[PDB]
Amino acid sequence: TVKKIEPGTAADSQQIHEEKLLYWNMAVRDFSILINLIKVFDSHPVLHVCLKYGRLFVEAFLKQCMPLLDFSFRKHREDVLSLLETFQLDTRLLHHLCGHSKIHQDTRLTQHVPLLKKTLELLVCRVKAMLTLNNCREAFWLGNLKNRDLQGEEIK
Amino acid sequence: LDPNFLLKVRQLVMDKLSSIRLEDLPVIIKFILHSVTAMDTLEVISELREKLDLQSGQSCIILLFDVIKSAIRYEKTISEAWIKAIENTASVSEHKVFDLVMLFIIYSTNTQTKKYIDRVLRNKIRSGCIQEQLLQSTFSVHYLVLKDMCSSILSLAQSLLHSLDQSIISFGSLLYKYAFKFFDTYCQQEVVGALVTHICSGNEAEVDTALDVLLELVVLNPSAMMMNAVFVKGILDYLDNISPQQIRKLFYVLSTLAFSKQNEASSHIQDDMHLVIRKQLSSTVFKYKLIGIIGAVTMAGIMAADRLSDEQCTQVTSLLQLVHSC
Amino acid sequence: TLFRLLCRDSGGETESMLLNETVPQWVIDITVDKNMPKFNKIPFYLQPHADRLSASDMLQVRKVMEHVYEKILAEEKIELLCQDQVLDPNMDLRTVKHFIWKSGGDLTLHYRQK
Amino acid sequence: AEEVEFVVEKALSMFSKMNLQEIPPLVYQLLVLSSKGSRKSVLEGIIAFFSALDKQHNEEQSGDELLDVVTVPSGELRHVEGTIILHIVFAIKLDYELGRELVKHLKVGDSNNNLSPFSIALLLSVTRIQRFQDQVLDLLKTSVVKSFKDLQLLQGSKFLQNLVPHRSYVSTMILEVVKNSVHSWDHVTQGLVELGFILMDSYGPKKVSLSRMPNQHACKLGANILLETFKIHEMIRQEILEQVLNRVVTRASSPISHFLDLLSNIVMYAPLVLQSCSSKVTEAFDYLSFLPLQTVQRLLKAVQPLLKVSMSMRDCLILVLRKAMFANQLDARKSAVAGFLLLLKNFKVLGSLLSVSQVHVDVHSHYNSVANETFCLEIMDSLRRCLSQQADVRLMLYEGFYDVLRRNSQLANSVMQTLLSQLKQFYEPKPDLLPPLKLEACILTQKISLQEPLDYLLCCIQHCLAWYKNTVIPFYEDLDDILESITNRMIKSELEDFELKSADFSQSTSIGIKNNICAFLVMGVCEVLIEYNFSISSFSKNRFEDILSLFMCYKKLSDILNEKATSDSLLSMKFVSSLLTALFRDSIQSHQESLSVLRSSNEFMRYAVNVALQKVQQLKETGHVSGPDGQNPEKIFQNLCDITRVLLWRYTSIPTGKSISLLCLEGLQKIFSAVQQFYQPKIQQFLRALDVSVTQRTAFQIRQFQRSLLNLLSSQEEDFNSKEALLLVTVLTSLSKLLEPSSPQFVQMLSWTSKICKENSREDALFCKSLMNLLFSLHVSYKSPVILLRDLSQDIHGHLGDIDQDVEVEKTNHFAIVNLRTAAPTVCLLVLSQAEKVLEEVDWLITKLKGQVPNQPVEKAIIMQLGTLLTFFHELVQTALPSGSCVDTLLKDLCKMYTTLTALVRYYLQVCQIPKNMEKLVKLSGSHLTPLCYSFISYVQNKSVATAMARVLRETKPIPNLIFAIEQYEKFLIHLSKKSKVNLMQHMKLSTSRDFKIK
């Protein structure tokens, strides 16, 4: 479903941009609920599906939603930051899933980690590119996230 | 002369290209093709592709193509520029008889464009640009110029038959059938010899398709296939790498060719086919015993096919009695 | 006949121009390029009388005699045989293959101490 | 399946026991039996047996033709191989699965050790099947290219060369397939000819660095294949010549230089060509008129060896060329003029010695000299009538008459009368009217263009007359009178009689274009008369005063045209060499007084040296020089030796627009580059003509330029001649290529360069970049530069600081050339390129080592290289590099570092069914690289129309690429830790991730 949402152009109606942004927010919420279910169901077939299709969801996000965020960031600023902040919580759980797979050394699981890690970092760099196109480079700033378990326990 | 002045007169030369006579078509084109620069090559040749219609009348057309063959004999750029014009075209209506004739000329004349002509031909056939009716019309009225390059056409036909798409395979089979129909005796033997190689190749797709072409040739021109039976009979020496389904088809075309006519030529093949099976039915090898049963039952079908005198009826009956006993 | 001339007339202007067109490559290779033709090689078997070797057709029996000697003064101690006949030390392998051998296989030579 | 595997395997044992002649009968039965059973093992066994059998035969064949221990004679060995190849080929024609197995088994980047002369010959014969034609020929093309890449990679490195014992190359393998094809392997030639043409078509020079050299080698192989196949096989030579002429006889203006050399080599065997393929040449001659002028001259010079010996070809060429003369169509008489000129400047004897019922009769008539002279004279009369055509046609005739007059002395009188008459059309014979020449008569207006190259006409007259007065003596007395008259009147001309200080001199107006064209003619005339007055009257003062005044006439008009806004100099290379020698190194009392006139003019010194530089530059760009004898390599080389000696002496004798000494150094650099590019086998003779072996003479010259660089460095920064220093390093770089690496002279060059880099701290970045490139070029051919690279990274870290901003990095100062200004982006970008070369070498070893299965010594060297390169990267990953291309290149190089580590882990994953050094390398990477890579990524990101979108989307790749490389490395470390049962992830910390959070 996400692959079929095109960003359109910057010359479209403001309500159209608002509707698509509202549409993307629902998709992220549905993604958030599905991804968060790996806490209770933490078997390999579930993790394999979540790990494999989490990458595909993020790839469609930075290919279909990010161009839309480029078009509508000044007029829609609170919505874009809210969308990115909520989606950031989901991507953090993807990072913890990647760490969980490598810690237990499951070859069937770790064989998806390198490609999801690249797309997870490619999303981070893509956000910065969005800010540069809107002359907000000094607004971008990174930070190192804490390593957590699937349940949420810090790994240290 | 002035490049701009030379350009204008050449434009006027090609302006009324449609309204000129037939005998002057060679010399007027002879002027244009040599009046071509490195950059102007692509633009000029595309115009000449469309500005030419071509629709001693039979001879002058041959003279026209003779000029083109000489003109591009030492010129790879012009020959390559022609194909780009055909490749760029995306409408079936624009493709004409003159289009297909030229594409074969570049293939035979210049060997440095064998691959590029093949790759574009696959695209046009697969996309539906080149059709059976275009190929049929091309051979029908311009087989005089195509006959000079029957070896080149058959090499193109053989390569097309090695493909995996039915559109390409069907066209390659048609290229075999039209070459057999319109060319002379010597190139017809090349067609049959090329088909026999495909049946002995080993590929299920090629053997099945080539056997269908052989059956079409036998039905279409039994007289021409009548004198090519020696090569068709040679496939019987390679039944080891042929599936039983294809063996039945191979016997069907052999049987329908042997009983197509009642002339003395057929009677030699008819008694020749009887003895081949007779010495397969009695073979100690079990596989050849089964091949003899398949071939003898197949022959009896054509032998007793309803369209039969008593002496034919007892002859087919004796064949069945032979199969029963063995 | 492509061209006929006397031996002394090759230096003339007319003859030399005609020679350039008529003389074939296989004569140019030896007379002009000064290339050397092939050396024919005859392999043969050394077996003890009671290891295949390939040598020039011009090789003398002495060379084969001394090779066996190093394997085991060479002239005095070693006598080479073929078809149960003695081989002359100065005789060459090409002559041995033609007269004494009288067989259609590779030339076999038998060595025995004198 | 298992049962048929045993029966074939047992038969492979019989291959080494049963007789050789019995093998082909066994192969046929075993090959047809393979149809219903195993297919790959059948072909692999046959190929493996004969590959070793051929190899053993080759080893024992080498040696004296005296008595040898030979198991299989070459004659029968090629017979059984040839018939067995035909057996395999026939099997493929009925199976199509055996053929696919053969291609898959012999598939190639990897060395593909299964390739052998037998397997290559087998592949070539397979190409007769149209289905496998393009597939197999593409395999052979890839094999030779990869083989040449391997050869070039080994020769360029010493570390890599030590570890790899030599292996044969596919290029060598194919050449002996041609050699063995003489033994009736006629089924191989057709695929052999096709491969040679594919190699020369795909990798021909497209001029219209790293990969250019192996591409030139693959094209050369195709020419070697095609030439050797031509000599041996008589039934394929007609197809070779026909195809060669097809690529040459075109108006497509495509690069055909490689095809012309092959055609020239084929026609060296002229009787071999005339016997079978002689019509192809005649049909090519028929198209000469339609070909452009450039093609005709190069094509005729290629078939010149054929024309030299064959009378019929010369008669056919004359017969065709005579029609082109009488042809009214233009652009075809130009080719006829070129045909007669080339044919008349090379052959002193020309001329011979039909309808349905017309036959030729062999008339036995003696050669007539008088008839030949009349024939040659008539051709020259036909060429004289062409002096009224376009200026292009006149240009060829002026350039060609000097060669014609030197070949045919009987036509000397015809040339002078032809040349003198043309001069009369433009020479003002009035002894007092100025200017001496009617410059308006050389101009055609219709657009204003040039009709008569008057300067080139005088150049041909002066050279031909000079040859006349020194050769045929042991009009001419009037030609000196005219040239003397032109000399004096041109000097006293006030530079206004030419209608030229600045009237218009524009590039758009008609009068401006005419003045510019007329400006070239008067300058060209001055050059020719400068050459003329030098030789006549010997070294007399009065003539030399006339040269300086003539030069000032040329220089003044050269200045006015240059300041408002070129062409080649008309001096011959022999004259420039002779002029320079007298102008600099002539010490004779009689000559001194006259030569002081020319030596006192500093601008004359500039002109004399610069023209010599122009002559050398034409050699590099074109391969030949413009002047007389400018296409004779022997005389060009002799002139280079004399020019070099003068330029070498002038630079060394006196130290320092640009000065004369700097010009001489610039010329020295060009000559050294040009000599090695063209006269490679004459390098010993080139260095001998300067006043043992090549290395000893080169070292003497090298030490001379070493001292000169020391003086520049010893001076102050403001006095540091940057232009000379870079030029000196370029000379040293070119000369150092001549030393043998395994020699004490090479070591001294490496030891001197290292000391210079460690002690001098010049501020110029271009000098530092050139000096370090010299050090690395020398060092790599000596040993691995990983220790050198590691020390340079510590200096870059010291000058640029650390990214932590809370710890202090100590300054190593290993090299003084790496200072604060050159540390980035000069040294950093330079060392990263060198480390990229190291990784490419190590990754080549692993690929070669992995596909092989001496595994023990190579593994230790690979781990030692990556262990040292880790410390190099560990220094740079924590350096405060500038945000430009230094960060982008380091990120890209770190990705290559981790890709190579993964390739090593995947190797041990394949081999481990883990040594201590591999344990330490994995532990070292996880303690000094991976955690610091994450710190570098945070450092880089934190500090900071349609094209703007492209730039930002390009900047988003490098960091995700590294993250994939690190994670891919840790993924395969988990696979290795499970297979080897030793936990390699205890050495690795947990991956650190970043979250964007906008302010």
Image (cartoon, coloured by chain):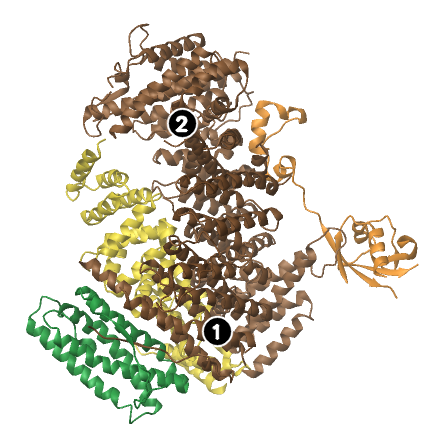
Chain colours: A green, B yellow, C orange, D brown
Q: Residue at x 43, y 49 (%)?
A: D768
SS at mark 2 in the image: helix
- Residue D70 sits in which quadrant? bottom right
Q: Where is D52 relative to D62, above or below?
A: below
Q: Is residue C103 left or right of residue D520?
A: right
Q: Where is D670 relative to D110, above or below?
A: above
- Disc 1 with disc 2 on a shared chain: yes
Q: What crowding class fits label 1: few (fewer than 14 Cα within 10 Å), some (14-19), or many (20 or more)?
A: some
Residue B279 visible in the current orientation:
no
x, y (%) of residue D113?
55, 65
Chain under label 2? D
Chain under label 1? D
- Inspect the image, locate mark 1, and give the three-letter code of the amino acid beneath it: Leu
x, y (%) of residue D135?
43, 62
- For disc 2, the marked residue is D606
- For disc 1, the marked residue is D924
SS at mark 1 in the image: helix
Number of dots carrying numbers: 2
